[PDB]
Length: 46
Image (cartoon, rainbow, N blue to C red):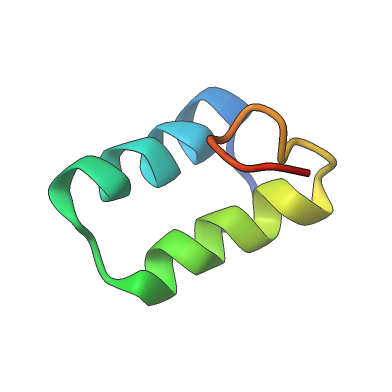
C-alpha cells in the first residue's frame, strides 16, 4: 500500500480485476497508481 513495486502494485489492480476483488482494493490500488502518474499502465483512459 505505502511501498511496493509498480509491477506488484499494478499486479494487484490487475489481479483484483480478474478475481473481482473488493472495489475498495481496486480503487485503492488505482488511487495509488493514479497519484503515481501510472494510470496509463492500467486499463484506464487518462
